[PDB]
Image (tube, rainbow, N blue to C red; front, side, top):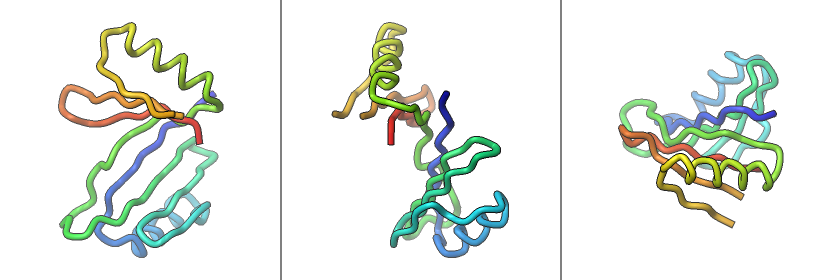
Length: 109
């Protein structure tokens, strides 16, 4: 089991927290200056809002797949490299980039 992560760079974190609390009917799980996390049950989603100074509009920061443990990250890392994709792991996460530049990370919290 896993869930997608969607990390957005937003020009107004406070307004965005308010909007997403209403959209998904739940408050943020974690709130800091500069970022907020929502753990949504349905639809399964990890939503990250990152404050972006002098971005005129919301844009994609990165995308992800949130998995249950480090072994799942390792499995994904091995699989993506096998399939010919350039990757970088961190010691848990592995990063790949799509052809138009969109970055993905498979990670465990």
